[PDB]
Length: 335
RNA sequence: ACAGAGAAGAUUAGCAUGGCCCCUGCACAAGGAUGACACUGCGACAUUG
Ligand SMILES: C[S@@+](CC[C@H](N)C(=O)[O-])C[C@H]1O[C@@H](n2cnc3c(N)ncnc32)[C@H](O)[C@@H]1O
Image (cartoon, rainbow, N blue to C red; front, side, top):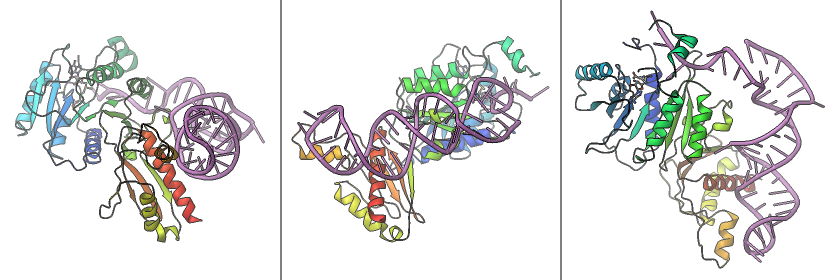
């Protein structure tokens, strides 16, 4: 009402589906536990908790800055019957953006939509069409810097996300992420007519989501992409026959732990045992007996292909080494 | 009714650069080969909004 007064945007729905895919692609053996969310900037609409409840039955905590917006969020949830699922908090301009858990479990994800102006003169200079809601010191980069700074002290929250409305933002915030050595992040490019958006999610945990969620197809921001998670190959009929035997001999001759999972073949590596360094260190008397770096990935076969999708790890060297070894394994059998 | 095109110049053919798999090697470096790759450079061109 104060700033939105329109339900036409489906970007809220797509942001929530991105949350769902980012969680369901990174859950694993973990049970379907109660999931609680955080909406920094719940606003007088609180669309994010509402559609994260009506769509996947999550729980939510909404942190607001404005008295009117806090009251309106309370009313909205009161006539929505998620009183027992969602909570709302009013905070002053100086409070930390991440509220205390207050005895419950730590949030599974934090998700925001930072304010995106700096001055009222700049408001008018760019677009003050007739309308501290849209004002902050630094913009969507300064707010993201605050969130990044406070995300050192709450690492239990798995998936931190932030939404950016200017392409120039992605360089700065991704540069700060690389300064703080957050390897597991991602950019998701949206599309609404001509408008584009950038969901720069970042986590401090091992689970890596799908490529379609961290690496956008367009190579415009190719310098800012996270590491690769999936490396696909194309097969030919003799390999499309001997694929099972070749994968067996590869994964068994290299001292590589593995086990099958129905229609998907798995792996569980606690040390690189396929690199040349692995066999040299095993064959040379040295104090270290393992090249560190965990990994979980799945090798599946679909229609003359082979996929190596990463599903765990803090280190990209292990994934790249396994991918290259597998590619050579295909090559030394196709011919 | 209020957050990427509204622009730097880009992308790309390409030439370098960098790791990765392979071989050689005790290590580091060092070297070849190859071909699955970029969070690195410069653009013989080619065309755009
Ligand atoms: C673009 S609005 C996000 C509104 C969101 N799209 C919604 O569902 O209404 C930016 C938000 O930043 C929040 N915000 C700004 N500074 C804050 C602070 N210090 N503490 C809490 N929230 C803050 C405001 O409450 C505001 O809702």
